Structure formats: C-alpha cells, structure tokens
RNA sequence: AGCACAGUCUUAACGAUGGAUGUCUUGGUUCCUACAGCGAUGAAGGCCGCAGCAAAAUGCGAUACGCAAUGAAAAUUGCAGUGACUGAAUCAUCAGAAUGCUGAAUGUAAACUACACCAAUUCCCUGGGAAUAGUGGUACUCCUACAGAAA
C-alpha cells in the first residue's frame, strides 16, 4: 500500500485487484468517501445505491448533469454510480471483516487512505464509418483502502542584546 | 469529536500504467574448413494416421513418439504401468527389418477413395492344408535381344 502508517496494529486494509467498473466514477465515489468513519461511509454508499444521496463529480465533471442532491457538497454536478458504488461497498465490507478479525472497533475506524488506480484496459472492438475498427476498451481499476482506529541556541552577545531589548521595553 | 471551499496548475514523497535501460542469451552472423545427388529399388513435396490417459511442434508409419541389432547401461516418471539386481528401463548408434495413401505418379481417372482389364493371390508344413474381393501387374518414349506376321 501507498500510505506511511508506522503502526499497522490500529489499521485495517482492504484491496480490489481488477474491478469491472469505470475508473472515473469509482474515483469520484472514493473522493466522496474520503476522511470518514467507516460505518458512515458504508451508509453513504448504501444511500447512493438507492438513489437518495449523490456523489459529487468534481474532478471528472465533463457532461455530468445537474442534480438536486449536489447542494449537500456545495457543488452543482453529481451522480449515483451504481455498479461502482456496489463494488466500493463490497471492499468496505471486506475491510470491516478484516478489522473484526483483528481487534479494531468498527465505530472508531476512519478511512485514512482510499486510493483508486486505473488497471490495464480490457480490449474490445467497435466498428465505425467506412470500414474502420476502433478500440472499445474498458477502464478497470485497482482499489486500495486503509481504515484506522482514531480517538535552541544562546550566544552571549545575542543574550546581551535580548536583555537590552527587554530593559528598553520595561 | 472537529477542521480544510471545490476545481486548474506546480513541486516532493509514495504508489499505478507501461516495458525503456541495464544484465544476461540452447539464436542469428559472416568467415574458414570438409564433404556433397536424391529418384520407377518410387524422391522432394503433400495429405492421412500413429501415445493409456495426447492439441501443436518434435518423432515415427498399420511392427507407427517406435521394432531388431550394436555401444552404453538402472532407471522411466504428471499419474498409470514397465523394468534392473544384463538382447529387458532409458539413452545413443543404426547397417537389419519395416516404410499408409499420394506425388515424376506411371492402368484410365480425379471437388471421385470412381473405374477397367490380366494374373486369382497369399500363407502354413515336409506334396497336402489353410485362407482372403485381398495382393501384384498393365503409362509414354527409348535401347539391346527374341518372337511371328507384313512389303
Ligand atoms: Mg483548493
Ligand atoms: Mg531394442
Ligand atoms: Mg544391449
Ligand atoms: Mg494412376
Ligand atoms: Mg465426377
């Protein structure tokens, strides 16, 4: 994992190797999640899956609509990336399980590192124009998630000068 | 429990993506040396097969990843199985045996496993007794010899 941890005893990690979900949506979801208690994050994910709360598309915001729920994050654009959300939820669950297996309280766990890297594209073919074959590739991803339990010089002359200054002030 | 606006750009650390560089290398490369034809005794090429579990390549040919014989010589192994305590397991060598169907392909054919005709053919035992629709042969040109006809 990418993060500098020091003590892995208070941390619980979870990974997703090559996910069949779009890199951008998933990234957005991750961003939305970040710096949150694990349970709260899970709840948020659930809500998004049921189309109650949206994730704000702030980075990859090209063409994404203009939802009502985006006002919650001071933004205008937002979406409900279902499959991606589900994937993320699964990973969260895994992380939770891992934590349980150790000795970490799930209530005091915060997501300290939610990384989404883009995996190698799954190549497919699309057919265009005047007999033209074009790449119809997917954008798979790796997801890395880390949860964590959260609760000169003197100089004599210089000294003299300082003293003088003090005296002056007085 | 709080707190960072967000985005865009930049820097550093740590990662992804990619396969550059470095290091290798049972390949190539050129040069040198040496030998140097295979085929109607059926070649090269091409099909079809062939393993217990078997696709390709490799190897081989209905004895089919090999038979015999020679020289080594205890293993072979994924499993199954087979052997040693030396013609046997495995290599190497290869001279003997064998070498499907084709292909110059040569009985006539060919998008045929089509079809003729002449031999019936083959094996066993020391003249009989068994077999199989199976095996041979039959092209065109030519040469030498023979044959009997023609002028
Ligand atoms: Mg900012
Ligand atoms: Mg032998
Ligand atoms: Mg021997
Ligand atoms: Mg013929
Ligand atoms: Mg015909």
Image (cartoon, coloured by chain):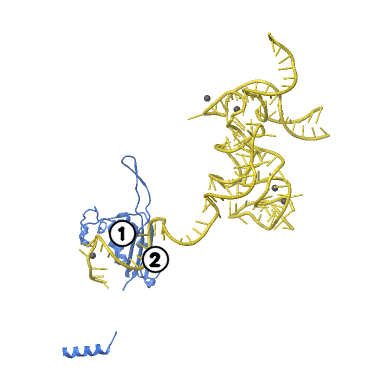
Quadrant of the snapshot with the C terminus of chain A: bottom left
- Rendered image quadrant of residue A113: bottom left
Please say if B67 is above or below A152. above
Q: Whole-Å distance between the Cαs marked 2 and 1?
A: 23 Å
Colour of chain B in the rendered structure image? yellow
Q: Position of residue B88 (x, y in %)?
A: 70, 51
Select label 2 or label 1 by which is in front.
1
Say which residue label 1 marks.
A27
Q: Position of residue B54 (x, y in %)?
A: 56, 45
Q: Residue at x 27, y 90 (%)?
A: A156
Neighbours of disc 1 within 10 Å: few (<14), some (14-19), many (20+): many
Say which residue label 2 marks.
A98
Colour of chain A in the rendered structure image? blue
Instruction: First in sequence, mark 2 or 1: give its number.
Output: 1
- In the picture, the disc for residue A9 is none
Q: Position of residue B71 (x, y in %)?
A: 72, 53
Q: Position of residue A167 (x, y in %)?
A: 18, 91
Is the distance from the Cβ of mark 1 to the nearest ligand 1 atom less than 8 Å?
Answer: no
- Rendered image quadrant of residue A87: bottom left
Report the image quarter containing ligand 4.
top right
Residues behind callouts 2 and 1 on a single chain: yes
Q: Secondary structure at mark 1?
A: helix
């Amino acid at each position: 994992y990418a993060k500098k941890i020091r003590n892995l005893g208070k941390c619980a990690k979870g990974a997703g190797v090559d996910l069949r979900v779009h890199f951008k949506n998933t990234y957005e979801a991750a961003r939305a999640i970040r710096r949150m208690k694990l349970l709260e994050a899970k709840k948020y994910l659930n809500d998004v899956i049921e189309k109650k709360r949206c994730v704000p598309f702030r980075k990859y915001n090209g063409g994404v609509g203009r939802t009502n729920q985006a006002k919650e994050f001071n933004h205008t654009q937002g979406r409900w990336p279902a499959k991606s959300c589900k994937f993320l939820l699964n990973i969260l669950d895994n992380v939770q399980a891992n934590a349980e297996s150790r000795n970490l309280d799930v209530s005091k766990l915060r997501l300290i590192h939610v990384m989404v890297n883009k995996a190698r594209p799954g190549r497919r073919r699309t057919y265009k124009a005047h007999g033209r074959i074009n790449p119809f590739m997917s954008s798979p991803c790796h997801i890395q998630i880390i949860a964590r339990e959260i609760n000169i010089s003197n100089q004599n002359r210089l000294k003299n000068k300082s003293v003088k200054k003090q005296q002056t002030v007085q």
